[PDB]
Amino acid sequence: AILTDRYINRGTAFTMEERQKLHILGRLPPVVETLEEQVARVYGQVKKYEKPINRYQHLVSVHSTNTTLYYATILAHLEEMLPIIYTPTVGEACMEYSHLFFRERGVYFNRLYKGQFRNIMRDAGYQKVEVVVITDGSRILGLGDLGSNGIGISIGKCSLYVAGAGIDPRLIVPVILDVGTNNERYLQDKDYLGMREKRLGDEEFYELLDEFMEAASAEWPNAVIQFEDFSNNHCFDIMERYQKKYRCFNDDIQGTGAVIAAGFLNAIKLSGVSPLQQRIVVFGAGSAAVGVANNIAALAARMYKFPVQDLVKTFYLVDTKGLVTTTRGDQLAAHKKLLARTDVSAEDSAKLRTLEEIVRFVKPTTLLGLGGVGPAFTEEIVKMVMQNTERPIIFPLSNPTSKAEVTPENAYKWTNGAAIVASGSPFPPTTIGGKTFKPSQGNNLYVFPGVGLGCALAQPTHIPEELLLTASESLNLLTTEGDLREGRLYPPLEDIHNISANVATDVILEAQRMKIDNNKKLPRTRDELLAFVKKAMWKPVYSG
Amino acid sequence: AILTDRYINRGTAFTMEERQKLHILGRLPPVVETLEEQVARVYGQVKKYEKPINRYQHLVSVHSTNTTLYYATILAHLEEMLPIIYTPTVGEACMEYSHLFFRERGVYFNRLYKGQFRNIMRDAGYQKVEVVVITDGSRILGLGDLGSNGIGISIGKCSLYVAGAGIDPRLIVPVILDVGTNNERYLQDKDYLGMREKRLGDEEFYELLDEFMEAASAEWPNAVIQFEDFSNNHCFDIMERYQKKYRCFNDDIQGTGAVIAAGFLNAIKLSGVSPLQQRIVVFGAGSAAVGVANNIAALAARMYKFPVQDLVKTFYLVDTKGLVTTTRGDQLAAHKKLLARTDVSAEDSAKLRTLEEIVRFVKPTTLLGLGGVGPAFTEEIVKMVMQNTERPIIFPLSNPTSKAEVTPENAYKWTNGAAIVASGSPFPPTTIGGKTFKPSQGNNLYVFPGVGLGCALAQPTHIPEELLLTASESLNLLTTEGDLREGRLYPPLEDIHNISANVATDVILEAQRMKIDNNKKLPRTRDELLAFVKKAMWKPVYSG
Ligand SMILES: O=C(Nc1cccc(S(=O)(=O)Nc2ccc(OC(F)(F)F)cc2)c1)c1cc(F)cc(F)c1
Ligand SMILES: O=C(Nc1cccc(S(=O)(=O)Nc2ccc(OC(F)(F)F)cc2)c1)c1cc(F)cc(F)c1
């Protein structure tokens, strides 16, 4: 009974005396382990499996049986587990092994339940829910429509709030809004269990998502609503529609830009080449890429009080046509106009089409890789940036590893160790003349859990851009003089509870400053607040 | 809540109306399936996995989530699932993936709990337990001592009673008696959770197993105690110690011989060469091999009332020295003396050492392979048996497939389709001149579940050899004139519920005849009893 409840089950960590008192002697093998010992054992069971998917499968069974031991194992091996319990293994689990999510707590909405969303939420009988992750399985990167099987993404993202910021696992809810799927295999699959129809048009999409947002605000009024893995046709428009009326954010848009900005500003500090001296090529010009550039500018403006106009003029935006300029003769998308050069002639614009010739002309000190078109940061291009700065900042952020603008290894090799690198993926260290270099990974885990924990405590009426900017600055500042001396751009991933506690404290203080905080119990000074936030976090240890 | 209880959970088989009434709308994807549809889906999820162990792993997750759907899938695909859910996959799961059994109901005994066995049983809080499978992980075949990890064998054997004879899954208990392990890897393994010591001596072994047998008879008085996968130093002695005082049997010894005897007698019928005309080489002379020969003799004596002495003289026992004879000049083990030739000279015995020369001299009509020494039934040997009968009976029963005396394919090929074959493993059909041949598999599943179900209903004071002989004859008789016309030696495996119902009926009637039956509610005429037994069986269908 104790054993069959994954929240209180301790398995072999029940002492002999506990086993007699609880009447479970002879329900376990006789060895008694500490949690630490159970973690080392589970870690061995995981590494016995070869393929990421089989490792995920084993971990799902641990989560089903002993939740405390699951989260304890993730926290002890976080850098190594991350690619198994989320991107990119979780997407493969959704696409071909969706049965791995059947047993998980989860809430399914579709048009058949129109008008009943609030009843379905009430019926789930959750207490004071703090975090709700919602997807429609459409995919931010637009690859592999998962439809209903998108529930696996919400389940995996919810587990990262629990591991990263000690959101209590009983107080988090994964949600799929099934509005159909354009996945042709799934539409013909006899074993697809979701709505077997093409994705709904915008009017019906927004009718169901409006009902979702209103139901959640009434039935789960304490919750942060986080949008995950929505396609580009909707994700930006969703934030515009809801950002002021509901407590909501989108991690792919707002999280990514907070994390990259914090790392980029620490790269600037190590470079010696100060922010107004940086010449930054933004390779890629989607809404997301422009969003990150704007987040870098907003952060440098907050931290340093340079005029934001002067920071915007450090950016050279490159789209598929070439350098984005006002003299190019094309009609620019709204999002490209802000970062468009005003200082480049029509004649020069005509000769600024390939990344090689753009780099030669611009003489950048930074390359930001947000391009999603493979390895465009060639050896020749990296050698040219070496002419312009002693410390080239090179950020190949396009995912996955095959779409990356350059390998950290090549970046370090070509610069003889001078490159300051951040990556969107983990990479092993590179050694050059006995000296070791490792890229700093801008993982989204640095920001969303702390935002969730801060918004859970502070209960703000909404999440304005001030709170994401505060979280970005908080993260930047947690990189210690020592971390910086070793070339690290972020605090260490394995210190995520402390990082989340700090990010959360800083978010609450910003909400208090703006007077949007609904929880009057919280300390309002940083030292006392930080202590309070750390005590509020759920810890994966045997409690009782 | 309904969903988290594996006994009542129906998953997607809950109708839309049921989902509203039970307040679980939005806890499932929206498709509604019948059980049949769920089975086809689970069957596809299983075949997506390549290796037997990964298939077992998926099935363990089904068993954990929806028990009705698990048993429904096994029953629909029984011949194909059998090698995944028991021998030989289950042993590999015990040896290297013992975590697959952690979540299962199971009872662990060891010397540390001496004097508390009855308290541990009471504390498990089972109702009217019907079947208890116990092992010590020593292994009947003496390969791969599993120690504590032997619990996986008891768990898999218990699932075969539920699938085979509709023992209610709540009324069956898997047990490991951990008396240590001689597995050197395990003794040094930091993740072994069992008693980390060499196997106890006989005196302490029997102290703990006596306490087990007495505790079970008091706390689980309705149960059949089945011994599984005990080593040869103990398994025979255990039956001698307990057979009269407790309701117990050993499937490896008693089950195997019941199944092989039933098949062998049907092989005799197809051969035309009647039982007193058979000349049978018993290749292998362990206690087990001799037990099977004695079970064949006892069955032919029951069915046909030939003097058993005349049946015993149809057997030519071959041990590692050669033909077992009284003139050989060695001191015979007790178990070999019964089947020893009295009709062969010292001089002939000296020239009867190789199987080839023994076959040439004996001119057998049957070869029984119980030898465990690879493929000794050579083409030359099979050609010689063709000189002695138009229908050679060839039974390569040694496990696994590599230790087998001959492949059914070779047997059929070498005899041009004349061979009557039973196997200890499933084999695909062989086609010769457009005519198809398939060996009859003597699976233990034909007998133990029906014995368990019969002993569960009849509640006999004990299980004397009469009840195993009745079960053997029952099985033999269920092979229909039609089955026999197609060369089948057993009723079809997929008809296991009917086979178990019949075997059980016949066992009860024998217990009633002997007046050892404690349940006075049962019909005492076969037609009415059979109907009653079928109604008592738990069925893997959604009930409520
Ligand atoms: O908790 C139980 N058993 C247990 C036996 C050994 C060890 C442990 S443990 O908690 O100490 N370790 C552990 C756990 C589960 C894991 O995942 C996996 F392997 F089961 F998939 C891995 C390790 C736990 C248990 C739970 C029940 F609901 C019923 C029951 F009868 C037993
Ligand atoms: O039963 C639940 N979900 C379910 C979702 C789709 C289908 C089904 S099903 O029962 O129709 N099929 C099915 C099942 C489990 C299987 O095994 C495996 F994949 F989970 F390992 C395979 C198939 C079942 C469920 C159980 C809970 F305890 C909590 C919860 F929130 C949901």
Image (cartoon, coloured by chain):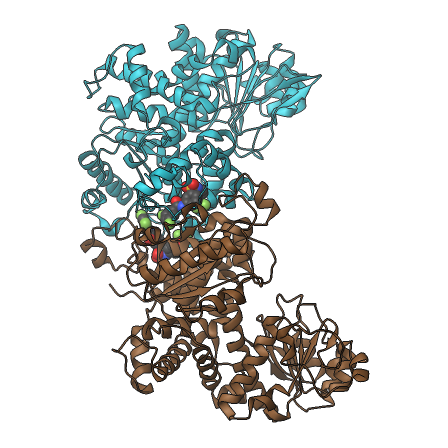
Chain colours: A brown, B cyan
**Residue A116 horizontal/vertical position (percent):** 36, 49
Image quadrant where one finds the C terminus of chain A: bottom left
Q: Nearer the viewer, residue A411 or A141?
A: A141
Front residue of this view, candidates A299 and B446 = A299
Residue B197 can be seen, yes or no: no
B421 relative to B147, above or below? above
Q: Please count the marks in the image.
A: 0
Q: Where in the figure is residue A508, as x and y percent of width and height? A: 36, 79
Find residue B305 and report its horizontal and vertical position in percent. 39, 5
The answer to whether residue B219 is above or below residue A173 is above
Answer whether residue B156 is visible to the viewer in this image. yes
Q: Nearer the viewer, residue A232 or B520?
A: A232
Compared with B288, B209 (above or below) is below
On screen, residue A387 versus residue A35, left or right, reads right
Which residue is depicted at the point 29% across and 21% down?
A: B464
Query: Residue visible at 24% across and 40% down?
Result: B212
Residue at position x 60%, y 12% in the image? B391
Indicate whether B544 appears above or below A82: above
The location of residue A299, given as percent across then percent down, is 51, 85
